[PDB]
Image (cartoon, coloured by chain):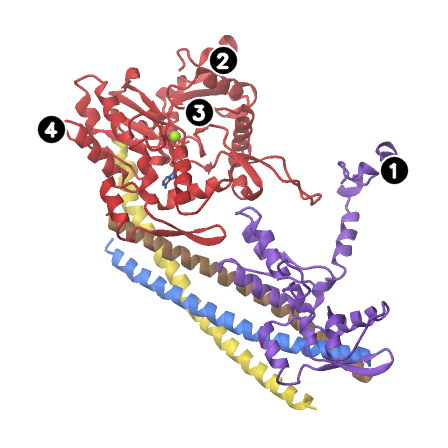
Chain colours: A yellow, B red, C purple, D blue, E brown
Amino acid sequence: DFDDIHRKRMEKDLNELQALIEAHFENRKKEEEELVSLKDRIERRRAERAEQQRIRNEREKERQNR
Amino acid sequence: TTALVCDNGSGLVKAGFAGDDAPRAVFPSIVGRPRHQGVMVGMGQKDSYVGDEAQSKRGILTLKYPIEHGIITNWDDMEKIWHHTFYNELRVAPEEHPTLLTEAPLNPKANREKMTQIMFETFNVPAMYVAIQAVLSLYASGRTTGIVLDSGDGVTHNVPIYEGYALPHAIMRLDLAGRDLTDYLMKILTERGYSFVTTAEREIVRDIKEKLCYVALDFENEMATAASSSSLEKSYELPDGQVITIGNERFRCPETLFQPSFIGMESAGIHETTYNSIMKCDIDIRKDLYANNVLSGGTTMYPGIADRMQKEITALAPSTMKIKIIAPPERKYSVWIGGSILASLSTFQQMWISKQEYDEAGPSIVHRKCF
Amino acid sequence: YLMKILTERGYSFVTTAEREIVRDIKEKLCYVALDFENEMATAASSSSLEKSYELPDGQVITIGNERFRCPETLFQPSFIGMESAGIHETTYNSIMKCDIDIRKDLYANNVLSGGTTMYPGIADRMQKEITALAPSTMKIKIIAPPERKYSVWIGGSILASLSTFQQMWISKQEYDEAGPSIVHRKCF
Amino acid sequence: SDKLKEAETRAEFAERSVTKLEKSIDDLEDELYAQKLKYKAISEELDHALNDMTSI
Amino acid sequence: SDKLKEAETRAEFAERSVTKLEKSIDDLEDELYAQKLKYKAISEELDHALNDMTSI
Ligand SMILES: Nc1ncnc2c1ncn2[C@@H]1O[C@H](COP(=O)(O)OP(=O)(O)O)[C@@H](O)[C@H]1O
Ligand SMILES: [Mg+2]
C-alpha cells in the first residue's frame, strides 16, 4: 500500500499536463484563426450582396417610378 | 467476470465496472411523475422520468428523491432507479455480475436487509456485498490509518480507523449535509427578494450553491467586509434571464457546517465532531489520526474548507501535534474509486455473499460474518 | 371600431349589411404599424398613406390614418374602452404564470394563428413588443405560417387522421348511458 | 383588376419587407463576425498564455 | 391577362425569396447565440480562474 500512489499520480502529473497543453494548442490553432478568416470572407460576400441589392433596388425603382 | 461497483448515495448515483478510475455513469437520483394534464395525443409521454432525463423535463415534473438521509424511504422508486442504472446507463444485465453497494454507518438494519433482498430476488445478481462508505474513501487515499470525514449530500459521518482496525465506539454520525445547506440557502435568498418554492427550483438553488458559495476562513471578518465594500457580490443568470446578485449569502450558506445552530440543530459543527471523534480513541493513536485527517464526499468541495477546518482543529488540538488535512482533488468520487479498488482485490474475492448462502439463511445473512 | 372611426371623414355605415362592406375595407386596406407614434406623425404631414377603395356602387373613399388605427386596438384595448392589456402583454403575462424552467422554450416557440393575425406587419410589431418586455438574453421568435387562417382546421384534420386518437370519440352508446354531461367526463 | 391590384400591392409589401430583411441579415452577420473576432482575440490571449505554460 | 401573369410570377419569386431569407436568418441566429453563450461561459470560467488564483 501507498506504493501505487506514485504509479497513479506521477503518470498524470506530467502526461495529463502535456496532453492538455497539446489539446489547447491544437484547438486554438484550428479554431481562432480559421474563424476570423471565415468571418472576414463572409463579410466580403455580405458587402457584395449589399452592392447587388442596391443596384437592383435602384434600377427597379427607376423603371417602376410612374 | 467483472464486478459492478454501484454506489447509491443520496443525490447522485455513481456506478461503473470495477477496476477503472472514474464511474461510468453519474446522474441525479430523482424520480418525477408529471403533474399537469397533457393534451397532445401520441406524444409518447411516460409515467415517470428517472435519472438525468428528469433534470431536463423538470419544468413540468415533481421531482422527489427516494433517499432522505442515508436511509431509503420509498422502495418502489429506489427499485426503479436501480433498474434504470443497470439497464440503460450501463446496459449490462445483472444476472452475470457481482454488485458492491455502499451504505452509511449506523443505518437501520431493515434498510440493508431490504436492499439485499431486492438485489437477490428482483435483479437476481450472482453475489452482492455491502460496505461502509468511509472505509472505501480511506482505500482511495492509499492510506491504512486516518479519520475520514465523509460529508455527503444526505448524511455526514466521521469514521476513525487505525492500522486497519476500525473503532466502532468512535463513529460520530451527524445528519447535516448538502441537502440541508440547499434548503438553508433557499431560505436566506428570500432576504433579497428571490423566492424559490417549487421542487424544481430547488435544483436551481443547488446550482447556485455549487457555483458561487465558498467557506470563509474567518466568519466575523467576512461578515464585516461584505457589509462595507461590494467586492463579494457575484451575479448569476437564472435559466430564463433576470440575473441575481448574491451578497453575503455566499459564505453564510456553507457556514452552517461549522455552526449547526443556524438551521436550529443543536450539535456541534464538523470542526468539533472530528475532534470529539478523535478524543474518544485511545491515547496512543491520537497523533496518527491528527496527522492523517481525510476529507471526502461531495459537500467537502467548497473552496476554502481545507483551511478553515485545519485552523479550527489546530485551535482545539494540543499545540504540539501536527494537524494535516488530506483533500485530494478527486474528492467527489473518492468513495467510488475506493470501491473499485476494493472490488479489484484478490484477497476480497471470497467475501461476497454468494446466492446459495442467502438461500440458506435468508436476508439476515448480511449482519452475519459476511458483513 | 373601424366603422366608428370612418365617420370622422363623412362615411356613415349603419345597416347590418354595410358591416360587411366595412369588414372588406378592413381586410383589404388596414395594416399594423411597427411604431404607432411615428406613423401618426407621418400620416398627419405627408399623404403617401391615403389608399382609396371603391364601394359596391362607385363613390370611391379615401382612408387616411384610419388604416393603422383600426388594428392598433389589439395592442391598446383602451381605444374601444376595454380595460385589459393588449395582445402583446397578455402573452407575456401568460408566459410568466408558467414555471420558471419552461419559459425559454415558450419564448422561442410563440405561435400565431386565427384569422385576425393576418394583418400585414403584425409578426414584427408583436416581436418588438415582447422583446421590449422580455429579458434581454432570451431569444424571441414568432411563428407565423402563411396558412394562418386555416391553421386550426388543418390541425383538426391531422388530429382526426391519427390512429392513436381513434378510440377517444364519444360513442353514441356512451351518450345514451350518461346523458349529454358525458362531454365533461374522461372523454373530454 | 382586383387580382392585379392585390398582387402588385402585396408584392410591394414583399419588396419592402425583404429589403428590411436584408438590412437585418447584414447587421446580424457583421455583428456575429465582430463578436467572433473578439472571441478569437481572446483565444490568442489564451494561446499566448499557453505558450507561457509551455514552461510546462 | 399578360400583366396578371407577370405580376403573379414576380410575386411568387419574391415570396420564395422571403421564406429562404427567413430560414437563413434563423440559422445564423442560432449559431450567433451559441457563440454568445460560449463567450459568456469562457468569460465566467476565466473569472473563476482569476478567483482560484486569488485563493492560491
Ligand atoms: N463543486 C461543488 N461545490 C459545492 N458543493 C457541491 C459540489 N459538488 C457537489 N456538491 C454538493 O454535494 C452533493 C453531492 O454529494 P455526493 O458526494 O454526490 O453525495 P453522495 O454521498 O450521496 O454521493 C450535491 O448535492 C451538492 O450539494
Ligand atoms: Mg457518499
Pinpoint residue C17: horizontal percent, then vertical percent: 86, 69
Q: Which residue is mark 1?
A: C172
Q: Nearer the viewer, mark 1 or mark 3?
A: 1
State which chain disc 3 sits on: B
Helix, strand or loop status at disc 2: helix
Kindly report which numbered mark, 4 or 1, lies closer to the viewer in this rendering: 1
Ligand 2 is found in the corner quadrant, namely: top left
SS at mark 1 in the image: helix
**How far apart in space, not on screen, are marks 2 and 4 (Cα)?**
49 Å
Tell me which chain the residue with mark 2 is part of: B
Q: Residues under labels 4 and 3: Cα distance?
A: 41 Å
Query: Do the residues indicated by labels 2 and 4 lie within the same chain of the protein?
Result: yes
Please, what is the three-letter code of the amino acid marked with disc 2? Pro
Amino acid of disc 1: Lys
Q: Earlier in the sequence, mark 2 or mark 4?
A: 4
List the residue tagged with mark 2.
B363
Give the residue at mark 3: B101
Q: Sequence-wise, which precedes: disc 2 or disc 3?
A: 3
Specify few, some or many for label 2: CA neighbours under 10 Å numbering under 14, 14-19, or 20 or more.
some
Residue highlighted by disc 4: B320
